[PDB]
Length: 292
Image 1: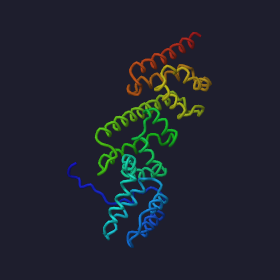
Image 2 (image 1 turned 90 degrees about the vertical axis):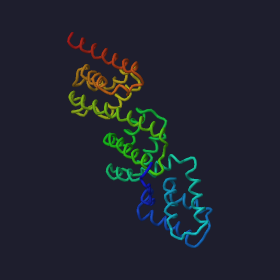
Image 3 (image 1 turned 60 degrees about the horizontal axis):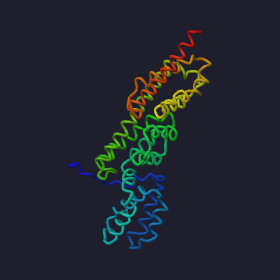
Image 4 (image 1 turned 45 degrees about the horizontal axis):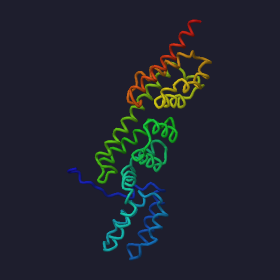
């Protein structure tokens, strides 16, 4: 570890369902039903699950209830065993939701987004089985154009914290796969940024006829389906022709692909296909334009 005394008190502050007062009552009702007077734990579970549907929140509520200074005695055992039932087979998802709660609140307030949506986001990222491009397309769709870069920062900050937690969502090897996933995502952001600068110098976005988001998606599809670059660019061409010569828009894509991280494509072979097609497009356009 091996010297950080993790941790760890403060469970209630990591609960993302409701309001500080709305959560505070809920925890008291569970303190009132009842560790102080000596009930009775069956269907008390359905009360727990009714107040907090999310397992991360459910676990945090019981950990707070485990703070009561009674501290008798078999009640500890019953509280800790309900914790095991909720967590069992869901360790990853629970631990990720807990470990990223403060970041979700931090970024939630910054992005003007609901924290629990960011919690779902980080869980989805470490537990999903979708590609880097699909993941990027999903975030773009879910959170918006404005939030596309910030969302990857939130995941990175959540990952950092998760790895430093006393109970991380993954083991070393699994975080290794997550780290690789994240760097690949960051490469996509890098081309996203490169691509945006190329559209600026081309001014293909100034008038507002073309949307930066749809243009981005077009570039993302090229990373996925290089052989269909020509078809992918069809709807762009139908609009750009009004003020831009075909070769300008094709060059914008060629150069963006040229100077972007190679690893965004499935392989170098697939990257060559994209470059060869876009060059063929640029070349054909120029010859048609100057002659005549």
